[PDB]
Image 1 (cartoon, rainbow over the protein chains, first blue to last red):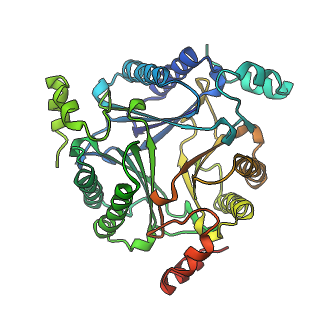
Image 2 (cartoon, each protein chain N blue to C red; image 1 turned 135 degrees about the vertical axis):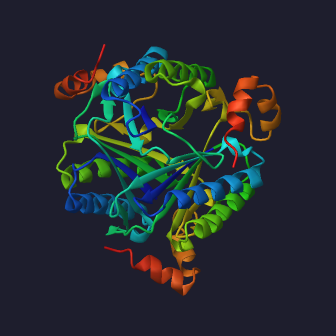
Length: 146
Length: 145
Length: 145
């Protein structure tokens, strides 16, 4: 997946960004089984005041998570995963849950590429990972934090 | 909804951003019935020259609106809403309509969270809001303009 | 289409951004027949360190291309197009392919506006273009490299 995380500039320190990315990545690995290194978290910072709710200019405490996933998972599991992102980002970013918005979009795995390779169907990551070259396996394995 | 609005740095002042956000938000409530406070407008600014059309580097006068919606509305209504966003953003941002691009993407409401809660289906916002806790209703209600 | 290209600040020079935009645009036109001027490439730069893979902070060498397309093309063609984007962006940016991520999303053409006009079905860009006003055609036509 790619989790695009929209936040205000200076809301999250480097350590807070790491914790938020860990929270999201752990949630995705834990509920889907997808290897850690296949989850990207991409922080998009803008100056505070660029977010409007109901036309009302917001401060720096809003977070929007746009998660981009492969088609193929149940609505039940997507709901658990969105809820766990809400709960765990709330803790990691020290932000009240009413400030957190999370949308998931899905596409066929056949039109998604990570590390220059087309993704497999959900749940077939082991088989796919074993038919990768040694060098590609090694590169992906460096992108794992517990 | 979340409307991601991609503009060049400095093309919209704070006042023009408020006007553009108000235009989009009024359009969305007016045509869908969704309460004002459920519409987010999220400005993403980049330096002039980061947009290319046909390979041609652009100035600061381009706008791309990526609207993210719940599934469930008609093509007719989505067309009227995209057109009204073109018309009203043209006036609010003082930009010619030919500079405006608008794409709508839809997801099941069941995978869409706002204010920490899952959204209802597109016509059920009234009863959904009523059955939120009082502190949640109060917090959403602070976001009306 | 709109190709949203997420890169680190300063990783691409203006020249490299032009090259990357031309690589993507030329790929899209060559494989789909869609005119040059209908393809937008929109660079979104953020400071290095804002990208995490598996929880590991990255340097400035990651690129994520989010292409937004009309519904109607085959999985075969979308696959060829994504592969050609990986290949041609790798050359244009001098970035190894392992750093390149590419996702395509699709929406109905009826909820898709470019140059203030609703798009036609894929393959029908010819008729559609011919029925635009002459001023609208002239404006579009300037966006060819």
